[PDB]
Amino acid sequence: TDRVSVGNLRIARVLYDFVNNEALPGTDIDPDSFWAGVDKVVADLTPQNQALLNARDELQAQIDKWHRRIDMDAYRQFLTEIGYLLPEPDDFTITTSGVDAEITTTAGPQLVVPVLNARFALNAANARWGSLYDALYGTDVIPETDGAEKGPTYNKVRGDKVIAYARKFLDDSVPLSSGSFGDATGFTVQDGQLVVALPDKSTGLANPGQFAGYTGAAESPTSVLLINHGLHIEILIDPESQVGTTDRAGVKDVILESAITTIMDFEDSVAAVDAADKVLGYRNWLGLNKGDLAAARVLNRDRNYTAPGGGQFTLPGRSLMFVRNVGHLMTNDAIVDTDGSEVFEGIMDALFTGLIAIHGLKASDVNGPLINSRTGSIYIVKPKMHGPAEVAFTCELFSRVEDVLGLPQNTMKIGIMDEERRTTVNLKACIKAAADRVVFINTGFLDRTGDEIHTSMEAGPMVRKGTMKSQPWILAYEDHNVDAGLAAGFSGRAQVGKGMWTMTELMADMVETKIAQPRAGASTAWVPSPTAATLHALHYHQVDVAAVQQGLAGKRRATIEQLLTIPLAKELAWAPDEIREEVDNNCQSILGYVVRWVDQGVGASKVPDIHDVALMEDRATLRISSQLLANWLRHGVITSADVRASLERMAPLVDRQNAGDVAYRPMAPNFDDSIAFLAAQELILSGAQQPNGYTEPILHRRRREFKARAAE
Ligand SMILES: O=C(O)CCc1nc2ccccc2[nH]c1=O
Ligand SMILES: [Mg+2]
Ligand SMILES: [Mg+2]
Ligand SMILES: [Mg+2]
Ligand SMILES: [Mg+2]
Ligand SMILES: [Mg+2]
Ligand SMILES: [Mg+2]
Ligand SMILES: [Mg+2]
Ligand SMILES: [Mg+2]
């Protein structure tokens, strides 16, 4: 037994040592008082945590039975009687205070990254600023048409298209008084105003207030800092660079303020099934908050400029960090009680990520340099909550953690993910439950659709996964989320977020279509990579989110009936080949993700889909796919032979898609010999029995089984 006893707790040594030697020192928290507080919080809050999970099961059994025995009036009457659909509270304004400008004020891209991957976490934090030239040149936003494709070395024709794209962007975002940036000859700062040399004349900006600063001398600036819709744009000037020599004004690059905030994730993008895994995550979270995290490589320093009217100012070189804790469901054996019962992981995350975040509020040799929150807040995204009482519980959890940490009450702020149906239909009350802590709400596709399928599992066969994206329930869910946030005063106070673009290489399509989200009044939305953050930033220059929000406020665009419109497939709406395609699709999604999760403990990566399109999904992809297949199985759309045959067809496909990975362990031809293959099979076959369709219990068990076999 490798555990430390503290009150009723038996703490894994690796965790206990991490906290004492790394997390605690520099916080001024007395270590014995901390550990006593951990024991007391776990003892006090565990019963309610369990009570809430029981209530999920109780409500769902009632819903299963109701469906087992189409009319909307009877259905919502039913949901109301069982306490699933609660009355809408009175109108109110959130009272959350001490929030940084990146959240209250700036609209822009939001990156989410697996905290267990230090290099990715570092790149994400550094992604507050990104190269537009690199993003345009390196992706298909500039088509690889004849002559303009990227080879082993610099293609000037392609670069010239990159340059022109960016010139057009500057014209659109920071218009000159006359002429185009495409005719620029040079830049100078005269009388604290930006002057752009043109061929036949000279010109300032149409709105000189968009001029924000510069580097080097006003005579010949090395860069020119502009602002639009709250976001900075820096024109780098160096006619001696590879591309500067080719440019008419010697422009080297255009740098965009990109990932304004980043979510460091402990939940669905990481595989962490024991104390050693949790410690890897906590240690990286620690390094980020101290500012000394280094990989293979380090965090960027802040950026120095001269204001138009002279005098120096500094801009943050890094993304403001949130941390995403796990939700209320799972336990982890990082801590067990006397009976050997595992402790609630969400409770542990609040205590440990909260402790660690104190370093990000400080700057010394002990706590590293670099401050995360200027206003003294800790930003925690709380996923997978079901309804307002589960939000209230999170409030109580954070309050008790603050007390243990010696922090001011309401220091720990909550990002409310709206990704469960019972939260969706009671969203206003969920926000009201956290009215003095809430700094965001957001929507998604996968997790929310996963819950949609599980909740109405007994209703009938569901439409295909692709179809879900355009279903009435989900479009109302998207608008209702914005409506509730705006009605509660989020504009100027808290983020209203939308979902992830998963197609990592389809940047042209993202740039074309993702603009719909800020057009919808979302002050942020999720991107999979620093490159995608820079490109998505374009949308926020193109759309005035603040103005969109002002025009939406007070509107009620969704009905409860729309929200409750179950995505049931019409009476036999598929051909055999369409059914086959959807089974293969889902089995491939499950296998492609699971094999990396169970075998290598990777919970996010570019996974080729069935059409070889690279997707960067998290564990929610598993929840939707396994629930859909379990549903089709449940209602006789497919057979158990169909499922097994697809898994066996797609498995070697997955193996093939993983050529080029040295640590990869093939699943075919001995399927029942691969723990990953069996995990994937189990997720489908036992899908209908999982609490709310959640995949963690199975995935965690299988990864743990794999670790034990690898050490035997
Ligand atoms: O559709 C959904 O609900 C899930 C969204 C999502 N979150 C991610 C977080 C970190 C890394 C990759 C991710 N991919 C994703 O699709
Ligand atoms: Mg300077
Ligand atoms: Mg620090
Ligand atoms: Mg989710
Ligand atoms: Mg939408
Ligand atoms: Mg409302
Ligand atoms: Mg505008
Ligand atoms: Mg805004
Ligand atoms: Mg059940």
Image (spheres, rainbow, N blue to C red):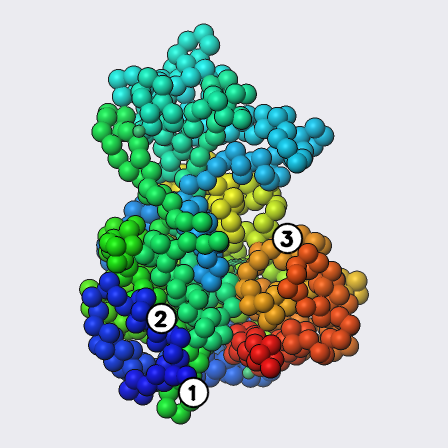
Type of amino acid at the residue the image marks with label 2 = Phe
From the image, tell me which residue sits under label 3. Answer: 614
Q: In the rendered image, which quarter is residue 338 located in?
A: bottom left
* Real-space CA distance between mark 3 and mark 2, rounded to the nearest whole angstrom: 37 Å
Please say whether residue 339 is visible from this viewpoint: yes
Q: Which mark is residue 88?
A: none
What kind of element bears circle 3?
strand
Going from N to C along the chain, the mark reached first, 1 or 2, is: 1
From the image, tell me which residue sits under label 2. Answer: 18
Type of amino acid at the residue the image marks with label 1 = Thr
**Badge 1 vs badge 2, beta-carbon distance below 8 Å:** no
Type of amino acid at the residue the image marks with label 3 = Ala
Q: x, y (%) of residue 83?
A: 41, 78
Q: Which mark is residue 1?
A: 1
Q: Residue at x 39, y 55 (%)?
A: 293
Q: Residues within 10 Å of mark 2 (few under 14, many from 20)?
A: some
Q: Nearer the viewer, mark 3 or mark 2?
A: 2
**Badge 3 vs badge 2, beta-carbon distance below 8 Å:** no
Q: Nearer the viewer, mark 3 or mark 1?
A: 1
Q: x, y (%) of residue 19?
A: 32, 71
Q: x, y (%) of residue 686?
A: 62, 80
Q: Residues within 10 Å of mark 3 (few under 14, many from 20)?
A: some
